[PDB]
Length: 46
Image 1 (tube, rainbow, N blue to C red):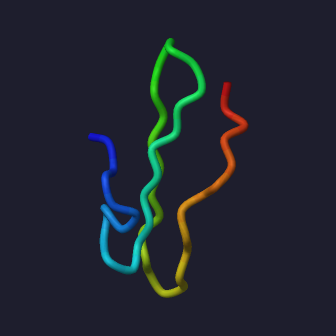
Image 2: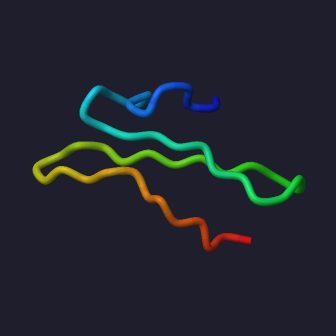
């Protein structure tokens, strides 16, 4: 379920597939409700 385009979730929304190690893969996406919220550019998860 990797996000190809930036706005995979939606045109206004943003999606970005994260991945640090080979143990597992992390994905993210923010829904646009009330207030706009862009996808996170940080990946402290490890």
